[PDB]
Image (tube, coloured by chain):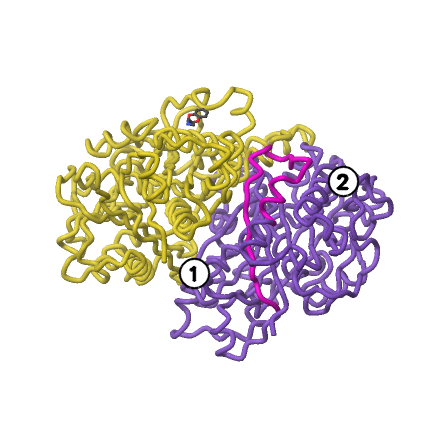
Chain colours: A yellow, B purple
């Protein structure tokens, strides 16, 4: 059989807040974390805005000397990781440290550090490159640094599945636990790609909204006026825990992780198939994994990136999977407020999906002023919607056509 | 319940050849793939050699029009994946495409690509960034591009765990099959970090051999005169397959994958503990995973990087895990010849471990002229050793204290 897996801790940095309760407050209020990027000259760029983390103090987590060694994406991951473990009340002992592992990932990793060490390399040559460049930039260093700080000796790994990283990190962490390889895992993702190379990289593929005049209105999933996604920074971390382990130590359980679906589109490098056939298979796989009928699903945290083709594919995939229940369920994109945290997107959207269970409210899809053709579902336009939510889905569809779905259920 | 997993296909680019057999003949003949580097000018660098892939012809695999858009690491990953799938005899169909996934990883990913696009950003501005920069550079696109070309709609992901990437990738792809999430996975990794930032970054940390006047003698695992690892490029992919599915289609089976271990050292960001404590935990998890008596292990393919601390820690780990039987088994580092393919190390070395079982020979550790204090095991100095091998183990250890062990045995 299979052990059940519960959420006992959550941590986050978002464009909405420096922790979960502040971010969730922004979500339910419909606030935007999008704004022109500061302390960066973007004159020559077609996009000049996104979701920055505002006022982050790494010295709440790290000495200034240890933070200097580490790319912002790693700092963000450690901050969410540290928040999550503390949120869980968990006490690490010699008796259980071998049973606690980490799977924190990144889409893109250390661009900002890579850009700054390039400056030195090109200007002054190879000897001005930092000694800490490699371990300070590689994606498995949130997992590494976290495991070293807390004495975690369980499964230590990192995923990098572009915009699906957060969803895949959590899902596969839940497997580790379910199949008895670990009793506890810290899982999710972090991202800081708002450098030249990120805005330029995504800018060159014309993947980004270029609505520089109204940055708060740029991210407008399923609206007829959307012109691409909004690039955002942050981290999410959940503490995943075997149910009996959680009950024994008297843990507060937010919710149960019942289902994880993966699939591949095998279609295109950056664009989904128009009918969302891959997101449909992935959701069906997640619901089968959870032993649930599609009818039982109440709330979907959509990928909902605000790209023409991505938004429309997700409607086709929901209508396909859910048939006559697809109007009954509520589906929103919190990217309408946060923008697209890429590899952290699924970590923070898992947390929003768990909080929708706790608080019995669908987050809004803000900026959905004029739904596009066939976007006739309950997309929770403009304002939060209190309702019954027993089961909640979080979807992530990324480059390479890599799909992930998480199923959360109320736990009592 | 838990299914058995066998190797039906393998593929490789190494510094010793453009496939498996050509690389293997070099391994058995104690040939070095290490040479001064020619694809760029390294006079400002403290280390000017490595294991390059020689005469790689991407137009054996890909149209030049697609090849141009992709980092060499992805080209290398696809070349090894394509070989492995062809070598498997597997035929992809509507009936089985949902059950065939891919997990091809990398340590650092498209560093060359990110460097070149950085140069363009700094010298010429953001409008000279390739539209292919992102999908052409991010680590999950070996998994992405493979799935698209072959139509693999199974689990689609990528691991980034530094120098452990290949072992973890192979090990967790086996767990996918073991637990029924897939019947087939293509798993391994690819690295091409031989650019300014690579040799520069590893140079800045003083990790690399600087034996520039004798590059073939630089990588000398467990030799008293070792002075850092040698940086090498390439790819390894295997087709992992449920046993009954392999039997059902008359698949040739190289060997069985009976054991996977992970652990975290939780010691240091880049230094292994001198006692090999995390390594020992990892190998013990793997042998317990395979239900084996440690005395059944005949051959260990060591991580064996040719760093002072790494090499001694491995001896300590092996002595501690294997006690007196540590003196009966054969251990070698093929890094003595290939150098360190970082994220791809685990993938090529897993294939060497399988060929050690097929051909009943321990590959040599070349350059082991003066074994260091305490390095008194059978490390197969200088020359291949024909011997009985039923059980073969492949170890990797990475930055972040991340450990991986794979256990293989003959299948009849
Ligand atoms: C063990 N629970 C506390 C976590 C979160 O707060 C931390 C902050 C800094 C360093 C370690 C930390 O550990």
Q: Is residue B249 visible?
A: yes
Q: Which mark is residue B312?
A: none
Membership of A103 in magenta stretch: no
Give the quadrant of the N terminus of chain A: bottom left
**Residue A19 percent across, percent down from the top left:** 33, 28
Name the mark nearer the viewer: 1 or 2. Answer: 1
User: Disc count in the image?
Assistant: 2
Up/down of B90 relative to B198, above or below: below
Report ligand 1 position as a quadrant.
top left
In the image: residue A8, left or right of residue B302: left
In the image: residue A136, left or right of residue A166: right
In the image: residue A127, left or right of residue A240: right
In the image: residue B190, left or right of residue A269: right
Give the quadrant of the C terminus of chain A: top left
Instruction: Tell me if label 1 and label 2 are in contact, CB under 8 Å.
Output: no
**Residue at 15 percent of width and 37 percent of height:** A383
Q: Which residue is mark 1?
A: B179
Q: Which residues are magenta?
A: B255-283
Q: Residues within 10 Å of mark 2 (few under 14, many from 20)?
A: many
Q: Which mark is residue B209?
A: 2
**Residue at 34 percent of width and 53 percent of height:** A260
At mark 1, the secondary structure is loop
Name which quarter of the figure residue A189 lies in.
top left
Q: Of callouts 1 and 2, which one flags the residue occurring earlier in the amino acid sequence?
A: 1
Membership of B273 in magenta stretch: yes
**Residue at 64 percent of width and 37 percent of height:** B272
Identify which residue, A156 or A137, lies in the foreground.
A156
Identify which residue, B187 or B50, lies in the foreground.
B187
**Residue B231 percent across, percent down from the top left:** 70, 46
At mark 2, the secondary structure is loop
């Amino acid at each position: 059989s299979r052990r059940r897996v519960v959420i006992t801790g959550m941590g986050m940095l978002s464009p909405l807040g420096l922790d979960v309760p502040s971010s969730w407050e922004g979500i339910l209020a419909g606030r935007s974390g999008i704004a022109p990027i500061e302390h960066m000259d973007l004159s020559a760029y077609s996009t000049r805005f996104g979701g920055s983390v505002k006022g982050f103090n790494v010295e709440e987590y790290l000495s200034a000397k240890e933070a200097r060694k580490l790319d912002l994406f790693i700092q963000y991951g450690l901050a969410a990781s540290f928040q999550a473990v503390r949120d869980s009340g968990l006490e690490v002992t010699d008796a259980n440290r071998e049973r606690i592992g980490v799977s924190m990932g990144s889409g893109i990793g250390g661009l900002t550090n890579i850009e700054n060490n390039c400056r030195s390399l090109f200007e002054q040559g190879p000897r001005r490159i930092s000694p800490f460049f490699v371990p300070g930039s590689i994606i498995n260093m949130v997992s590494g640094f976290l495991s070293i700080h807390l004495g975690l000796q369980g499964p230590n790994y990192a995923l990098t599945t572009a915009q699906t990283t957060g969803t895949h990190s959590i899902g596969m962490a839940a497997r580790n636990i379910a199949y008895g390889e670990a009793d506890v895992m810290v899982a999710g993702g972090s991202e800081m790609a708002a450098c030249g190379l990120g805005l330029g990289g995504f800018g060159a593929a014309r993947a980004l909204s270029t609505r520089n005049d109204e940055p708060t209105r740029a991210s407008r999933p399923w609206d007829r006026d959307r012109d691409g996604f909004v690039l955002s920074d942050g981290s999410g971390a959940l503490v995943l825990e075997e149910l009996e382990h959680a009950r024994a130590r008297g843990a507060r359980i937010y919710a149960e992780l019942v289902g994880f679906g993966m699939s591949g589109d095998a279609f295109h490098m950056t664009a989904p198939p128009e009918d969302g056939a891959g997101a449909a298979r992935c959701m069906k796989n997640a619901l089968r994994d959870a032993g649930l009928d599609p009818r039982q699903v109440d709330y979907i945290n959509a990928h909902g990136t605000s790209t023409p083709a991505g938004d429309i594919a997700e409607i086709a995939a929901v209508k396909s999977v859910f048939g006559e229940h697809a109007h009954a369920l509520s589906m929103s994109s919190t990217k309408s407020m946060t923008g697209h945290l890429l590899g952290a997107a699924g970590a923070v959207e898992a947390i929003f999906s768990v909080l929708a269970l706790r608080d019995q409210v669908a987050p809004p899809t803000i900026n959905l002023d004029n739904p596009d053709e066939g976007c006739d579902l309950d997309l929770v336009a403009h304002e939060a919607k209190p309702r019954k939510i027993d089961v909640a889905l979080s979807n992530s569809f990324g480059f390479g056509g890599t799909n992930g779905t998480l199923v959360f259920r109320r736990f009592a």
